[PDB]
Amino acid sequence: STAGKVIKCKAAVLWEEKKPFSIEEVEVAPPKAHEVRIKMVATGICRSDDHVVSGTLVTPLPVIAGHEAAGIVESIGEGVTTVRPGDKVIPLFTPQCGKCRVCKHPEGNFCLKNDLSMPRGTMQDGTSRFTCRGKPIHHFLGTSTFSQYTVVDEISVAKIDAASPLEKVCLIGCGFSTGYGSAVKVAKVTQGSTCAVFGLGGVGLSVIMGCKAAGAARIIGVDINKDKFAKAKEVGATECVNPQDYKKPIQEVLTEMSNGGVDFSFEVIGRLDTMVTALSCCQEAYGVSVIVGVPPDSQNLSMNPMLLLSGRTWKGAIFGGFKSKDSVPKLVADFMAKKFALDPLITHVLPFEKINEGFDLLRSGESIRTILTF
Amino acid sequence: STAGKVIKCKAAVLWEEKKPFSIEEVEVAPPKAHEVRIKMVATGICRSDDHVVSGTLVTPLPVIAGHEAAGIVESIGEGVTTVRPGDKVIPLFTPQCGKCRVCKHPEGNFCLKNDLSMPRGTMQDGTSRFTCRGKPIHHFLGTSTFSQYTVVDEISVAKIDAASPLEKVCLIGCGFSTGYGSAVKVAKVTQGSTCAVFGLGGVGLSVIMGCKAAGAARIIGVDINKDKFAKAKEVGATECVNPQDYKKPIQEVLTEMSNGGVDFSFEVIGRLDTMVTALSCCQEAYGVSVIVGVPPDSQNLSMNPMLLLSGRTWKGAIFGGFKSKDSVPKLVADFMAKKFALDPLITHVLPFEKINEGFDLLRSGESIRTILTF
Ligand SMILES: [Zn+2]
Ligand SMILES: [Zn+2]
Ligand SMILES: [Zn+2]
Ligand SMILES: [Zn+2]
């Protein structure tokens, strides 16, 4: 009954930088060929949406942010074959065109048809499917999840298990997959190993879960916030050290505990200094260090190349290294299996009209994760 | 007839820093348990021996440098089982104890019983087997190859094919294995791939040979010395670019030629800037960059962590990543097979008494490789 025409719903529009979201009434055009229209059930509030707000992550304004969510398909345009109206889904911030140099590469996952490198804030056709009173509103990463309805290209959507709690699995859209995959697919943690995770936030907790799934024998969780240590242990950290309690550099305290250094270290905070530190606390001969995120406004770090000469590996990734369309479905399946748990991460569920409030919880504080329900 | 007592031979002793080598008469004590005495047939002159001279690579003086050579066993001490008097060998700058955390690791190769990290300039027992007129002379990396006779621990020696041209295979002791292995074992180049090698010197030429053995489909050789380009092509480079001819940064010219960037890049010069450049000219989503060497006096490089975030890998290694004792024997076997050639690298053969002259050829110039014969 909306199957073939415009929709009128409320979306959180960012007109200007450093301005709160504006609950507005916008019209959502019907999906063109290979586009899919989804009715949002829940969306998480991720750090990267706040960067849009600061002007740190530069993308065309006004826009409709959000990228970590789950929904239900309302209508699909011409040529769509992967989803059907009524199907559960998760929109993908990192596409899967399935045909670029990267999609075909057995390891690569940063699909070339992504809108994060040189942001356009459009659909693959270069047009916006949103208007606010005659004014065109830009998309955010082919997602725009801070809307009751959104349109996404077919390469930016994944069909998941129909019995999926969408108020929980929305995590698989960013936060969880990003940390989880960093462990299991980027570092490729091995059983019996020792790992160090710098930052015990939500992505942080997801890395620990990965390291655990992977089979690590020890997981040192490091944060300067004692308070964050309980969940970490509950989720899998075997130990937790507060760099603030030692009279010496933790790379040292860390190299001493692991007797030589850890097998894998994770810098999940995005700090430059911490990036180097984690590189160092790693076994000099065969240690692997993974950078989970770096603020979009990061500067150059200072390092001694000698750190790599001994035998260390330094890696990075977007979306936990997962081939998005192939993998999302699988993470739900594993969750449905009772494999991993997602609850420990959800610290707040607010109705969607209270967005800006969610952002406050995020901005100055302890909010592991805030889920917005529609 | 020397089988169980001191020997008197000539060695190149470095008494002081920034002083030429002194052809001297020194006595070589007989091998203790698990030590082996070797009669040198030839030794290459490697860049790292000159660092000892500048004071850049800090090791106890006076010392007997050299570490890239081949010889014949004269006597073996108690408990030796791997070599027998008369056997061809290659002394190993990077040991193989076979029992440290690193020897047991399937990838690690930087044996923990190495003398490069915290140089002692002794034997595993902490004693020197050299004296010059009553004065003790230090060892260099468990090797000291600038001597007619040397003593090495059993973990620092490899037995090779008895039909081996030792005036050619001495290369497998440093120079060749270092570049070769960087390709075939550290980057683990794959067939059909595109590679970029920064620096067309000897290790440089060995990386190109590796990339070729490995099966690359394209090999861009980069150097600011047009003159070095012929051997590179002869040895395997499909193309050669001189950064000096473009009006733009080669990371760009390079990203444009490889249409996205190379699969693997090698920084074989040891320059900080070049280190970053090679990181960048690599496919953002799945490109691997390998650092073959860094001067022992290197400073911190400046970099944007964002380079790794997309999906790139940054690695380093000592001795081409090869498990020394296991591998050396195999590189001779492959050479004996007609697999790879070593000649193109040997640009100079000088009798050993003319050491300092070899160092001149090295120091200011084009000398791919200088082999010293005893
Ligand atoms: Zn693609
Ligand atoms: Zn996110
Ligand atoms: Zn060892
Ligand atoms: Zn060398």
Image (tube, coloured by chain):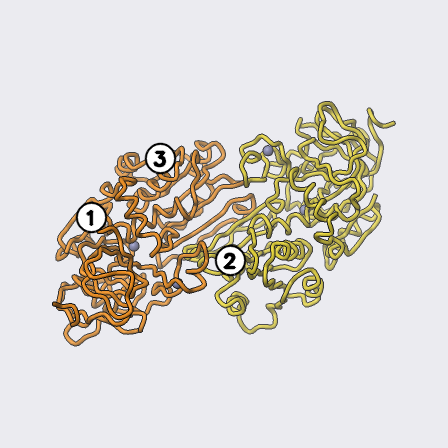
Chain colours: A yellow, B orange
Q: Kindly report the distance in space between the C-alpha atoms of the residues bearing marks 2 and 1.
A: 42 Å
Q: Position of residue B339 (x, y in %)?
A: 29, 40
**Disc number lying in front (3 or 2):** 2
Going from the N terminus, do you reach mark 1 or mark 3 first?
A: 1
Q: Position of residue A191 (x, y in %)?
A: 57, 57
In the rendered structure, the answer to whether residue B365 lies left or right of residue A95 reads: left
Count residues near mark 3 (Cα–Cα under 10 Å), then give few for <14, some for 14-19, many for 20+.
many
* The disc label shown at residue B54, or none: none
Q: Are marks 3 and 2 on the same chain?
A: no
The answer to whether the beta carbon of the residue marked 3 is less than 8 Å from any atom of ligand 4 is: no
Which image quarter holds the C terminus of chain A?
Answer: top right
Viewer-proximal residue among B374 and A78: B374
Tell me the residue that label 2 is attached to: A279
Residue A263 visible to an observer of this rendering: yes
Dot 2: what SS? Answer: helix
Tell me the residue that label 3 is attached to: B241
Disc 1 marks a residue whose amino acid type is Pro
The chain holding disc 1 is B
Q: Kindly report the distance in space between the C-alpha atoms of the residues bearing marks 1 and 3.
A: 35 Å
Which image quarter holds the N terminus of chain A?
Answer: top right
**Disc number lying in front (1 or 3):** 1
Tell me the residue that label 1 is attached to: B165
Question: Is A46 rendered above or below residue B73?
Answer: above
The chain holding disc 2 is A
Dot 3: what SS? Answer: strand
